[PDB]
Image (spheres, coloured by chain):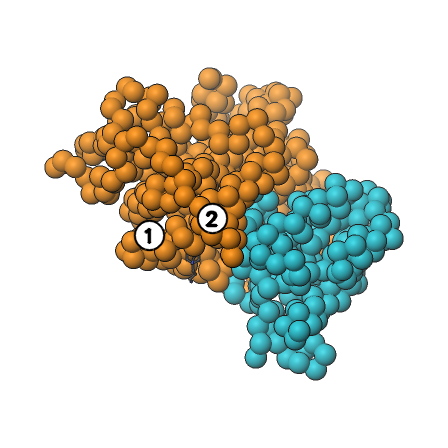
Amino acid sequence: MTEYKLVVVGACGVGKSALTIQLIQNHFVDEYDPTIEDSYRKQVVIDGETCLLDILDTAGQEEYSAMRDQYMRTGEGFLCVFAINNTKSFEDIHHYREQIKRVKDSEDVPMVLVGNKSDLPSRTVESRQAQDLARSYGIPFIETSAKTRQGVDDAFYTLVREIRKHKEK
Amino acid sequence: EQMRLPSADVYRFAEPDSEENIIFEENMQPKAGIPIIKAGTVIKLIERLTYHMYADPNFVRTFLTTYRSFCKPQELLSLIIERFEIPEPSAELKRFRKEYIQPVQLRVLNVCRHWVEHHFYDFERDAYLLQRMEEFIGTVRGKAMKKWVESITKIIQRKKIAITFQSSPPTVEWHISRPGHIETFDLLTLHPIEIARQLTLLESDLYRAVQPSELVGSVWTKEDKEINSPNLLKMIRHTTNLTLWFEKCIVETENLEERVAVVSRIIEILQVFQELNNFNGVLEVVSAMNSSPVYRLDHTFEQIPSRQKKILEEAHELSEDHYKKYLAKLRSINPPCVPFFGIYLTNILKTEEGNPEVLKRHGKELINFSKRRKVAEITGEIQQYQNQPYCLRVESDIKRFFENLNPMGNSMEKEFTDYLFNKSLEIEPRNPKPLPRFPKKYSYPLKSPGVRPSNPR
Ligand SMILES: NCCCc1ccc(Cl)cc1
Ligand SMILES: NCCCc1ccc(Cl)cc1
């Protein structure tokens, strides 16, 4: 069984947490203990291939700015996450992408852009702006809603598909 | 023979327990045999905080550490005053005074004592809250209460007001820089043992200054982080600064042989951090070596003696598989130590984000208390490593040298880390470019004095 090591990156105040939490937890238990091993590992079937996702989300450790390289080097694939009501988190994406390319020493690193919607303030980043950025990078864009589970599987599964397309070549 | 309290119309805490106001976990409270509260209405939580049948220190601590997400301080004080003021509905009455009113009043007083002793910041931040506490306490009448009333008053007064060892710490170690010659101090001129000792002291004090109030509610991630989590932030900035200093020391040493000495010395400091159980120190080194400017220096790494490769690799491996070996190692050592804080931060954040603030039962909203318990377990684990200090003498010049370290200078983050990376590229270019030579910058000897104490004692 193939194992994909995924890393979530993005600014604080964004629901990077909520994205990974909502993937891992069963859809109808709003419960989560991050101190146990099953909290970051999930078995899933994607395009008929059963596989194991291992998701690193360092949400809360954004201030340890010098540890980012270390954490990023552990991943094969990256979700670059911004909040659709925080323009700054969207403008910071360019920087996270550059750092990932430098850490992985590669111009073509499996990657998806994720815009997450939680609660107010209202939207400041139109999905068009994000599609345009994603397109300039040659990567998928997925928009998600934390609270409703919408988009969450799509974001992670799309990244896995990006890794599979990268591994073929 | 039950008890018979007043009507729920005249006293809100008389309301019976039901599925709509209080629910419990399956398991029972460790050491004490008390039911574990899962959720309840704020009225029911306050009833249980001050329960007549028994004392609940665990619940008191947990509640007082975490209540602010669901109840304002002023509201809490109002509620416990309401709790305290028990009307009467002489066989039934003497029993009721002695087995309900007096126990409950004592428990309220105990909450007040704990609140003021351990969470005085509520009062520092809201003087009117202290005003109300003081005039409530002055109101309290009975002779049964006097002792606790006087003790509370004594704590309040103490709180309004503005190191030596068990036996001998080891002798301070000097290498090339002599005592007092702060101008000469650098990575290679101070003794690697003493670098690790003095950084451990700094980092220990930084770890110990962080309070639960800086952590509960994930406040270090919010827009007021500098107001609410200043000690946590100073601690993290220290760590970041040292990591960056190590990277800088490495990549600005352009001569290969000298750079090998530099990296080698940093691994020696790591070894001492490891001996001291300074895990923050361990990881500030590991982070430097995994940084993009350092990690790529294959010509430097090739020349690191095999012993030190293994030391570094063991340390790196603590971080692998989501800190699996770090976690096990920390459980197994006794204080003093300096934990890596980041894990606690992520656990607290995900606990708060990953669980609902309330649960609903028969259409009624109950405060999810088990979520708060989980957060209080993490802050409790943090506090257990804060009690025991290191038996090491402070050296005030070496301490000052590391406090005033500023590898970034006036530069912003991006500018600085681009500078380190470009520097790495210059000193060891990408294949297929040949490796240049560079002149030596250090006019003193590079040989380490090693990591064993120089003298006996
Ligand atoms: N396997 C490479 C280890 C990463 C590393 C560590 C130290 C230095 Cl100087 C260069 C690279
Ligand atoms: N599990 C071996 C990984 C190899 C490695 C990676 C990073 C550093 Cl700092 C040292 C060794």
Give the residue at mark 2: B428
Residue B88 lies, in percent from the top left, at 63, 38
Instruction: Give the answer, above or below, for where B334 lies relative to B321.
Output: above
In-image side of A154 versus B352 (left or right): right
> Quadrant for ligand 2?
bottom left
Where is residue B401? Give x, y as percent: 38, 26
Q: Is mark 1 within 8 Å of ligand 1?
A: yes
Mark 2 is surrounded, within 10 Å at the Cα level, by few (under 14), some (14 to 19) or many (20 or more) other residues, namely many
Quarter of the image holding residue A56? Answer: bottom right
Nearest the eye: A127 or B264: B264
Residue B110 screen position, x and y as percent? 49, 36
**Which kind of residue does numbered mark 2 sit on?**
Glu
Task: Looking at the picture, tell me which residue is in the foreground, B407 or B237.
Answer: B407
Chain seen in cyan: A
User: What residue is at 66 percent from the left and 73 percent from the top?
Assistant: A169
Q: Amino acid at mark 1?
A: Ile
In the displayed orientation, state which residue is furthest to the bottom.
Answer: A48
